Image (cartoon, rainbow over the protein chains, first blue to last red):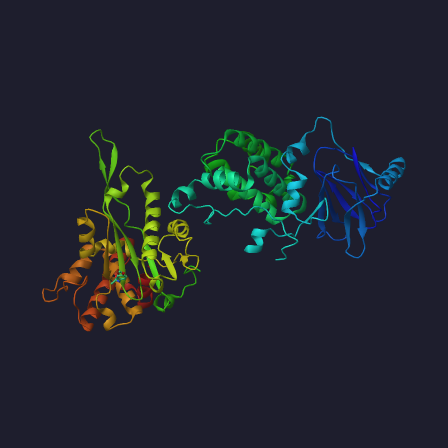
Length: 300
Length: 254
Ligand SMILES: COc1ccc(NC(C)=O)cc1
């Protein structure tokens, strides 16, 4: 059970750890988060109490290194840092744990929510979408643009999601214009799966990452990518049965976790109505259709 | 853009453009079968591809053989239209390729955009203009070449005949749209106006009669009267009681 200690909490802040969150007051004796489950990637996220525009965080894996948070009063944010001295890190964590200055990752035994949201998400693949190669953890925030958004500005601070464009030479074989436009199977199976992602696991990994960045940061480009990757599958007549069954599971848990009060900002009416009621896969997403009709019937 | 707020003058500038109308591509007669079901029989169609500045009409004749053994024909027709317009563009020298293609129906936008991905600098635009190009098949010589075709064929026309020798493109297009609107509204009455005077003929190489400038004014007047008469018949409106502002609005409003 790994630990992300904090030097201190000098500014009032809402701290998220995966799907959980808590409020820390200005100069509260808060020295971080313990009992973080090994075996999954995690996200620690922040929204300042005095300025809700400051919404940002770090994807990390405690298997990769010893990570801590320290507030930087110059840049005005909680920074993740790697501690290379193992024995200093263990000694600091031990003191904070003894003084009970840490909150415990509040995982219910029965509850597979986080595994279900991150099944296909790998820290090595996140570092390819978010490249700051000197760090083992990845910073994301609410404002970060995607490579596709930057084609339609700073190339270093960008989310390198795979560009999906239904009206692109990549999506449409010369001579198969109608076929490829009405049935996205070529674009999904040959261009995206065989060509770029190599396998459905990598495709689901980016889809899941895009959803999580949309939900935790309100990252608009991430929300566009999540919907484009759903629509590319739902708009294909030919999809392996294992991929349809897994997508139904993936979306079910995403729609389950989505806080109701954010459904107006995080769900695209056109895409969901098309995917569930008009697409080739309209009858293939049984679990997703049922939770969507029961939780968000207004949208549909 | 589109043509929402509208500048009509853009049609007559020196940027090559084409209107594409797909309303006559897929044409059927609906009939009863022996068992008393309903079936369709396709008849020959055409793509109406017009340069409004020059009058150049690229009439691609769509032979019924295109449809043989195909499904979802109303959908396919859009894509076949887009396939043929893209083939026409690719066939033209670079200096004759259009800068814009204006589709008369919004359903043609995606098909044409997808067929023209190789031409990112050619704008594909809709129009808020309600253009009467469906009535192309009311021009006898165009209907005749379409119905006689035994195979896919392209035929070239100047839909303005020799009018540009005497009038501007703006005025030629206005005359064409008035004539096509009248043929669309009351084909029989429109043809009687055009063809009833024994002394006025259609040149072998023309589509419309050889009217003097003064005769075109009379014909134009008679066509505007036909359109207003049919609007009164349709809506049960006493037209004899309307004003010129009222009358002017009803024709262009159309
Ligand atoms: C062979 O390529 C062309 C292009 C345009 C035209 N113009 C007319 C008179 O319709 C004719 C031929």
